[PDB]
Length: 271
Length: 271
Image (cartoon, rainbow over all chains, first blue to last red; front, side):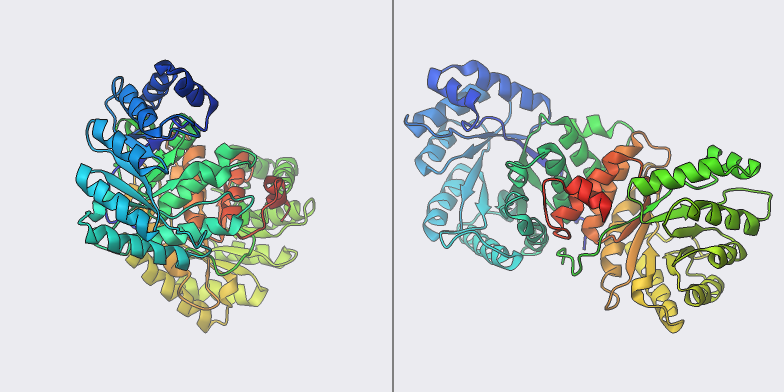
């Protein structure tokens, strides 16, 4: 049921080094490392376990941009990167320069993606995020999404990837334009945690639940608590949003995953 | 799973008219109706569906104190009362003066309580909160608590009380002194919602999760979101804590129980 089997620390993947934001995008354009480095530091200090790295829309060679981003980050912080790209050569270039064990963001359940990314994860001992979708489109239902999760699991397994290395992303969509999905995504998270022993892990791109809604921060933290209750293991999220992290910390203590003390808000951040 | 079967509005039971607080207690001592009336109004305005009414520790006749509290409240607001007392004569006196359909807070799973309160609920067409405990003591486990819930259900049913009228309180304890319980209480809520069709309802005395902890408000709202995700139907809670109510509102929209609009924080309060 809802009593978690494990007590692994919730994995926070800082979202901020993503060329969808203008500051990163203009850092990349200028080849200016300072914003990248400042954000790397800031997210590390706030408790991030991994840093998401996304080139954003560029007409430059994504391979060189990813390499630069990964080396620039890891020059100033001792964290691993969650390499976030639609381009597999870009991911592979990042993996070759990366120090320590990375995370790949992401493969879809599309056979020819799975066929490309899972060998990569295996080759470079990276974790890998699988998204519950494919070209047929956005799955509707928890049943749909769970079918794709099983497929991901079966492929991961056939490549020899441990379940501890595989993070299924059940695809949260914004609650204003796609409200009904949010509760289907909670039920998917719950079902994913049943599909193997050890279980696959689960992750969300959290800030998607609120894109273009009012009070994003309230919506983000409310859903993060719901999803953690459902069995979520990781999120790509705004680790600079102290209310958010305070909510996750509080949820993690309430799920008896870390032993209470009065300074748990600080402790959770150190773990 | 976690996709709720219904879409009933979450039931908020204002906690504040309780002689554990000094102001109420001294209002009762003085027979001064103004604080009672102000708090009744304030909780109504904030969205309460029911108002909890608890005499607190008194050496006066609890029967007269309850009657006075219920009439004083219902003179100024059109809400029902959740009559909160260890004394069955006090509850019955309140029921006789009460306008509309009340709620009884509470019976335990102790046979001789059940034997007294369930007839009362049936006689006066009141809802009734059943607590998962008995004299053997504080149940440890979700399994323990669920056994007591089943017992409550079986007794309710033998008295002819509909499941829609029966709110099982799975007994949340403070996370600093009894951390492990909080996740057992979530799993109990989930199991209670399986025990009949229609299901019994569930309720928590929410503010118990944080008694004598720091930042009670953060702990209270975090657990309320977790419990709602698990299938909670009602809470006795601080409806004057706008952050709390904002969290519940947000959870209720994320559970697809009320259709999103941009002003849902206001709408949820009107429903």
